[PDB]
Length: 86
Length: 66
Image 1 (cartoon, each protein chain N blue to C red):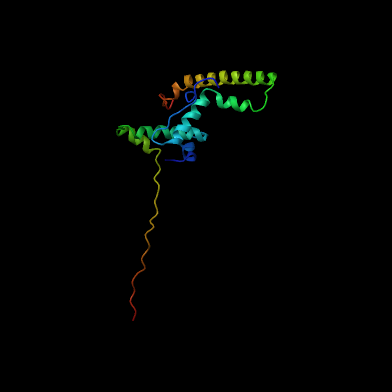
Image 2: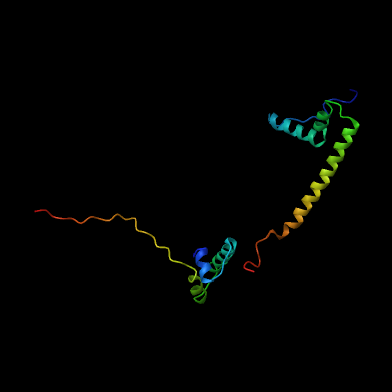
């Protein structure tokens, strides 16, 4: 309200491609967490519920990152069979 | 290639389906190489000739009347 306008969350259109400009804006707001934030704010999430979801999201990210690391590590041996027949 | 039931008789043993595949996968890997004469008599022991039937139509004889 007190800030300058047409700086925040503003994307310029290139060659009249408004679809690509909108997708870039949506990707910006998504990566910064604004889209999920706006959605969660339509109805009040109670503090006990927010902590439970934040704890679940933090544990799921850890488990997913740890499962990706294991697959990356254990995919080095995906090469062809060196001792086929034995 | 011979079928599992024919390999199971050359060996006189019982084989799984995957046991059969692994043996065949290993023979194909032997053909792709520069196999010599000694390495060719061995593979032919496991190649059974497949007889291809002729689909060509049999022609009736041409007869002559009185």
